Length: 312
Ligand SMILES: CC(=O)N[C@H]1[C@H](O[C@H]2C[C@@H](C(=O)NCCS(=O)(=O)O)[NH2+][C@@H]2CO)O[C@H](CO)[C@@H](OS(=O)(=O)O)[C@@H]1O
Ligand SMILES: CC(=O)N[C@@H]1[C@@H](O)[C@H](O[C@@H]2O[C@H](CO)[C@@H](O)[C@H](O)[C@H]2NC(C)=O)[C@@H](CO)O[C@@H]1O
Ligand SMILES: [Ca+2]
Image (tube, rainbow, N blue to C red; front, top):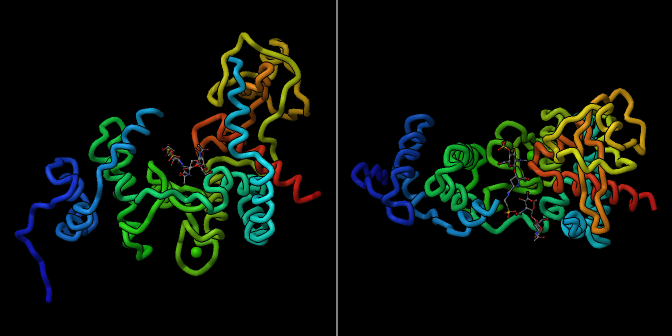
């Protein structure tokens, strides 16, 4: 009947003689009441995926922006985005009212992330997270905390840690939430009492809550294209310049910037030259989801492209 197996102190699998795995097991038992033998049986089935390690290590004008953009903004994609928007219009409108994050932004996020649920990932979250926690020193602490949180999520939401699949970094569902993002920002938007990242309605409200929690200002502008070139200045979402500095560099806003006294300098490689943008606070917020200028511009433009296609 009851099999404590106090003596089975040694697990097999790819993490058997791994000190990190043992320390992690100790932590989970001590800190959360996890049973060592149960956890060992789980981690013994965990796999050390070398590809997850090679991929994390791997992370002019030649048209760079255009190549990234065509991966997400195509007729097929925009069309699929319209379908997703109409199918979940109530959930999107309700997220707009509760969090102040517009439907196009959520449609854009979920679009760039999983093509509205068509590409959720094929890697078991446990394998990816265990690999990065135990065989990847550089970000071993971050990922260990992700693994720690994933295992508590499996317990709380009554999931099997081995059945859940996602990205090579362990991101999950429609919005590709990392375990800690789930813990801090996910919400039961569907109202069934359970926070499921694979439920389109939950992902929608969770993406909006994540945005609001990261500073999204309702009604404010994301980015404003500029007339002109400013080759002297450095660029990226991390940069910061006053409007006065940008004007003196040869730029003018195609749209009124209002009370915005500062902006970042975004530069997109459009093949024939460079396209300059005034990055406003809301664009910085989009990058809090995924630290990339290209990622955020794709999310924004796809959302806008889908928004237009609905009107037509
Ligand atoms: C919504 C969400 O959970 N965003 C998190 C993001 O996930 C990214 C990770 C990425 C991912 O899974 N990348 C793997 C690469 S591949 O596509 O499988 O090849 N997708 C997710 C959503 O955009 O990773 C960064 C950095 O870890 C996190 O920032 S941090 O807290 O400061 O660390 C951020 O919170
Ligand atoms: C080569 C290519 O075009 N790949 C696409 C992937 O980039 C997409 O994967 C998703 O990309 C975002 C942005 O980096 C990640 O944050 C997210 O985790 C990732 N999703 C998954 C499940 O791994 C994919 C979905 O749009 O579509 C292409 O395969
Ligand atoms: Ca739910």
